[PDB]
Image (tube, rainbow, N blue to C red):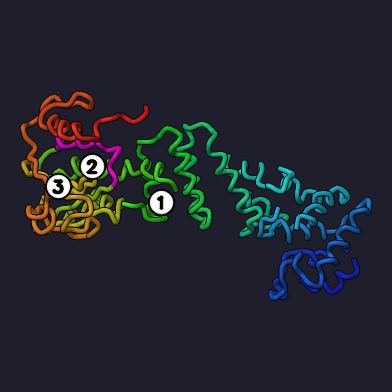
Amino acid sequence: RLEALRRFRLAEWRMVFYGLADNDPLYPDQPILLEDDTFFPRVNSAIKKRIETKTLKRRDWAALCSSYFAYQHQSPWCVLRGHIAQGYLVVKWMKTIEFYHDIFTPQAGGVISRQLLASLSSLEKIAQIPDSSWLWKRIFTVLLAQLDTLDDPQFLSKISWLLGLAAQWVRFRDDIMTATLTRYYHSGYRDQSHPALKQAALEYWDNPQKWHQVSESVAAMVRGWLAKQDLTHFFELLRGNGDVDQARLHYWLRFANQMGFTRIIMGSDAWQDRGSDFVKFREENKGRLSYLRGGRNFDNAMVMQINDYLFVEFSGTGNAMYAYQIGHAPFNPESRTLDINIHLKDQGRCALRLPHAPRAEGYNKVRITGWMLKYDDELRKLGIRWMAEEP
């Protein structure tokens, strides 16, 4: 195809077509078109010379498009972008760059991004854009920069598509996700569930307790569900042979906006539960769930991290909670197998022991009662307390 370059020195529509198209499958050793050593001045003149002609039907201009529409680097090199910016007037392939200059400035990515967000697919009739940072990046640096607008009864729906964009676009996966959660923060959904980002962000890279390399004011937003989901499931789904423990739930779900790390510990019968209910439970949060040894077949536990101390809670009604200092524990919280006595209930290695007595009645979110009233008093006298997030 690219043999037209030999006769391209002459300066009928398709005889010069492949003298300006994508380069250079025929000679891969040949560098980019405007860094060619032997054809740099030839194209700069021949393209210019054909412009002054009043009428043109040649396909070289559309061929000129492909070699710069699919141009990778983002220099906007713009000299031949200038000629094509004016060349399509005298040819009236005038539809080649109709919306390619939709913004008419070197900072491209105009309404071409608005078609997808509200093309990279329908524009292949003139030239294909699989990987060219001139259009590929600059069309997604706009549709992500416009997340700060558009109404939000369908923004949640648009994440599902926007998470879908992170599915095939491998490079934009670390750029869409980097800015999908940032807008999800400022929207007003600081503390409401969104498993799709929760799953997708965890899959794409590790959530500490790699995100810090986004900010730490936005990572903790969904961390409010790596904390809350570990609480809700533990006190409602992993209740063991007993009923739901509301008494331990409300007082502990209260302090969910400051929790940094959480980890559920399973039971013996839980892995003997062949039903998918615990299978998806073990699959939805893979890598955050662990096995339990040395305890009863229905025993359950948590590893809890707070601002100043590491906390352990158990599903057995009447078991005192064990507390460890942060970074000071006989067990690895990320270990897949743990023991109640060897690791969790090591009295010689634990710091604080407090039974859940006396029993509390009349519990409410703002009105506090019973043992957790004293539990609140011990913590309120020294620091963090109950504060509702900005409504």
The local secondary structure at tag 1 comes to loop
Tell me what residue is drawn at x 84 percent, y 52 percent. 87
Q: Quadrant of the C terminus?
A: top left
Say which of marks 2 and 1 sits in front: 1
Cα separation, mark 3 vs mark 2, equals: 17 Å
Report which residue position mark 1 lands on. Answer: 211
Badge 2 crowding class, 10 Å Cα cut-off, few under 14, some 14 to 19, many 20 or more, is many
Q: Earlier in the sequence, mark 1 or mark 3?
A: 1
Q: Position of residue 158 (x, y in %)?
A: 49, 40
Q: Nearer the viewer, residue 280 or 69?
A: 69
| Apparent side of residue 358 relative to residue 253 in the rendered image (left or right) | left
The local secondary structure at tag 2 comes to helix
Identity of the residue furthest to the front in this view: 382
* Residue 365 appears in view: yes
Q: Quadrant of residue 233?
A: top left
Disc number placed over residue 231 in the picture, else none? 2
Q: Position of residue 312 (x, y in %)?
A: 16, 47
Cα separation, mark 1 vs mark 3, equals: 28 Å
In this rendering, the answer to whether 348 lies above or below 229 is below
**Residue type at numbered disc 3:** Ala
Range shown magenta? 245-260
**Residue type at numbered disc 2:** Leu
Q: Nearer the viewer, residue 86 or 341?
A: 341
Badge 1 crowding class, 10 Å Cα cut-off, few under 14, some 14 to 19, many 20 or more, is some
Report which residue position mark 3 lands on. Answer: 323
